[PDB]
Image 1 (cartoon, helix red, strand yellow):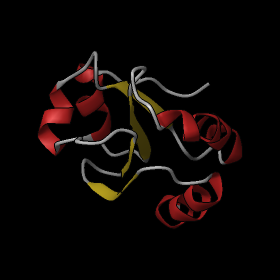
Image 2 (cartoon, rainbow, N blue to C red):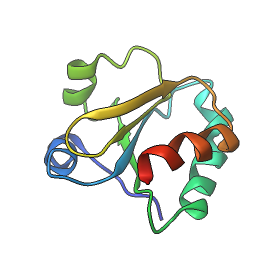
Image 3 (cartoon, rainbow, N blue to C red):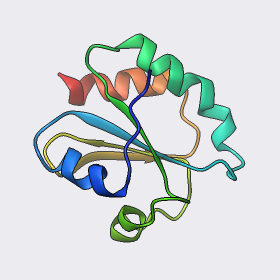
Image 4 (cartoon, rainbow, N blue to C red):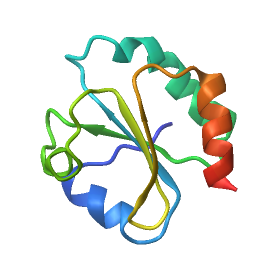
Length: 105
């Protein structure tokens, strides 16, 4: 199961001190379907390391205004209330797995 963050728990979650890859996506989005199954397989890949969380920026609009999430999908890794790496668009699971290997270690 992937994690599911939400406006209130979102910032209280990341700002503590915890590796969490927040996935910003929407059910009305077009090219988020491309990486849709790699993201759920991404939680199958590392699993005991990556918290692949899910914010609906449609439903929860507070953090999308802070960062300015202008084009979903948008993956951002937070380790201690600070996005170490923002990458967006379609990125294969192979691009993801090497990208997140650096920050998770």
